[PDB]
Image 1 (cartoon, protein in one colour):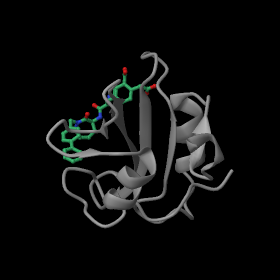
Image 2: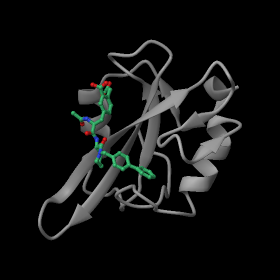
Image 3: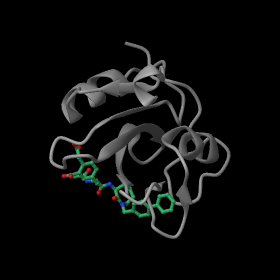
Length: 106
Ligand SMILES: CC(=O)N[C@@H](Cc1ccc(CC(=O)O)c(C(=O)O)c1)C(=O)N[C@H]1CCCCN(Cc2ccc(-c3ccccc3)cc2)C1=O
C-alpha cells in the first residue's frame, strides 16, 4: 500500500508541497508523492531542484495509474507499482530535474 510509504504525503496541496520542498537544507531530488489537486485517481511527484539560474526550486510531475495496472509519468516507461516507479526514478534522472534522492522533511 502506498499510504504506508513514508514518501506518500497523500492529500496536501501543491503550495504546501512547495513550502516543504523550498527548504534551503534540501539537496536536489528531495521529493514526495501526493494526490493531484485536479485529477481524481492521479498523483503528483513533487521534486526539489537547484541550479545557478533558478536557485532552489520545485517541479511537479503527474503520475498516471491505469485501471490496467501500470503507473507512469511517461506512457513509454511504466511500472507495476508506485514503489517501483519511485525506485526506478531514484536511479535514472531520464526526463526529471534530478533523480529522486531523499524524502522531504515535514
Ligand atoms: C503548472 C505545473 O507545474 N504543471 C506541471 C505538470 C502538473 C503537475 C501536477 C499537477 C497537479 C497538482 O499540482 O496538484 C498538474 C495539474 O493537473 O494541473 C500539472 C508541469 O508542467 N511540470 C513539468 C515538469 C518539468 C518538465 C516539463 N514537463 C513536461 C515533461 C517532460 C518530460 C517528462 C519526463 C519525466 C520522466 C521521464 C521522462 C519524461 C515529464 C514531464 C512538465 O510536465
